[PDB]
Amino acid sequence: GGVTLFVALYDYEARTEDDLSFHKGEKFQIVNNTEGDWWLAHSLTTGETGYIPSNYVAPVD
C-alpha cells in the first residue's frame, strides 16, 4: 500500500540535458519507470523532475 520512495546511494552529476544531478541521501518519487533503466523522478529536495539512473537509488524501507 502507498507509494515507494527511493533514496540515492551515491552522488551523481548529470551529463545530459534532462537528467538530474543529486546527492547521496536525496529522496525521490518515481514518476515513470516503464521506459528503461533511466527513470523519470521527482526530487523531494528540489521539486524538480528529470531522469535518474535507476541503479543509483534503492527503495526506502
Image (cartoon, grey):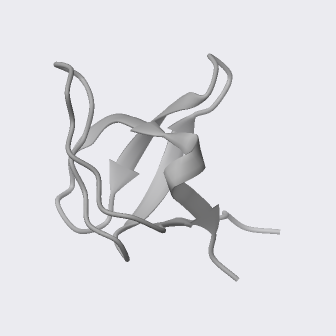
Position of residue 19 in the picture relative to residue 41 (left or right):
left
Residue at point 40%, 64% (across, down): 10
Which residue is farthest right? Answer: 1
Between 10 and 31, the one nearer to me in the picture: 10
Between 49 and 37, the one nearer to me in the picture: 37
Between 47 and 51, the one nearer to me in the picture: 51
Return the x and y of residue 9 as percentages of the image width and height.
48, 68
Indicate whether 25 appears above or below 48: below
Residue at point 36%, 48% (across, down): 42
Indicate whether 37 appears above or below 11: above
Indicate whether 11 appears above or below 51: below
Q: Which part of the image, by quadrant, shows the N terminus?
A: bottom right
Return the x and y of residue 18 as percentages of the image width and height.
24, 23
Q: Which part of the image, by quadrant, shows the C terminus?
A: bottom right
Residue at point 34%, 71% (across, down): 24
Position of residue 9 in the picture relative to residue 19 (left or right):
right
Q: Quadrant of residue 60?
A: bottom right
